[PDB]
Amino acid sequence: SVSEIQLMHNLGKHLNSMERVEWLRKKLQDVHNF
Amino acid sequence: VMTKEEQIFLLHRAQAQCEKRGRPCLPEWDHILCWPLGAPGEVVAVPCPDYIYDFNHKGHAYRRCDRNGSWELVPGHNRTWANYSECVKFLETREREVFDRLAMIYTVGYSVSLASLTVAVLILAYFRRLHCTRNYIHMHLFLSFMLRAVSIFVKDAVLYSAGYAGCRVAVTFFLYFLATNYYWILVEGLYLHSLIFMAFFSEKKYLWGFTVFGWGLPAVFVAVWVSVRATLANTGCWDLSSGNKKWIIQVPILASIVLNFILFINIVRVLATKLRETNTRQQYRKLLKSTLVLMPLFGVHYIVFMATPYTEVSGTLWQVQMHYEMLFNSFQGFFVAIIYCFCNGEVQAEIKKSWSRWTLAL
Image 1 (cartoon, rainbow over the protein chains, first blue to last red):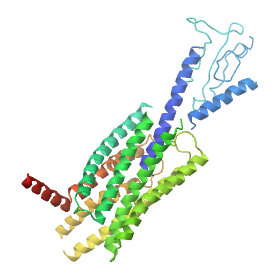
Image 2 (image 1 turned 180 degrees about the vertical axis):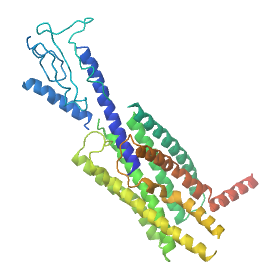
Image 3 (image 1 turned 120 degrees about the horizontal axis):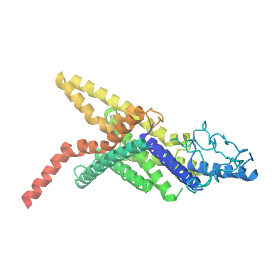
Image 4 (image 1 turned 120 degrees about the vertical axis):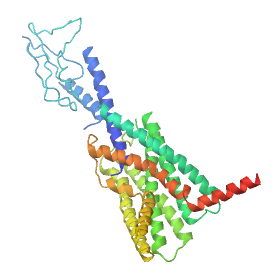
């Protein structure tokens, strides 16, 4: 497969996961502070 | 796997069911999840919710209420005591480190290639002697490498710094500039094959035809991909892959590599034949030297990992492939400029004459 495009797709998944994980992290603090 | 948008959507749907909905302890749980009940003065024992993405669903929240149906509150004045701390014992530094490592390698390699190619383009353009159909295609190939590199830098700046127009424009240009560079490598290979295997040439026609094929055809593939993306998914940036539609652009680029590879082997064949006709160790040395110089031009190194589908990031094959490609792809322009412009005999002779005349006049 084309490497540059493949790397681009991997970066999108990686960054999207970070947003989800950081979204989970702040939700964890909010419920802990509930 | 599901994206951030799905999680936002599913949470809204999750809370929707909350609305469509000792002592039972009443809802004493949270405002995010949707098991609104404390059970009859007992451990809730509700498994870790499966509507969240991973969440190790096999686990349990183990929320509890006691006394006779009342929560156990105010430990240190905290309220709504919960026990899912062990449920969130789940799931990145390794992936980011290698991603950054690959970023620095190709950014450095692309930067040197741009500097080398820019000097190469200026050299070819200024000297009138070097003006030839062969050199025009070389200038086109050298340029295509530049637009490829600068767009990658532009894409990196936009991405590193949500479906805005600028994000799409950067992505589509990067793919188009990547495709044209690949096809211009094919154009150079096809042009060489035509010269050797054809006894007649028409510069006025073939030169324009090669230019149109190198530039126009990649635009068509990008245009159809853009049209498909806009009218099928049109979600956020095009940085993410929505399925097999990426093959609209990937497949033609790969189809070029094999064709160029076949031409490369064929060109080596005539080199092995002609040297055999003129006579040995020397002949092998020239053939090997000729093969090495032509390798960067024809993009032979691309064939090593051409047919590899999407492999998981946490894998040896993925790591070696990214390091291998991001090193040779970045430095391919630098090698091509060195061999075919800086090391070119005509360029060296032309530079020597101009410098000698300028020094004598001065």
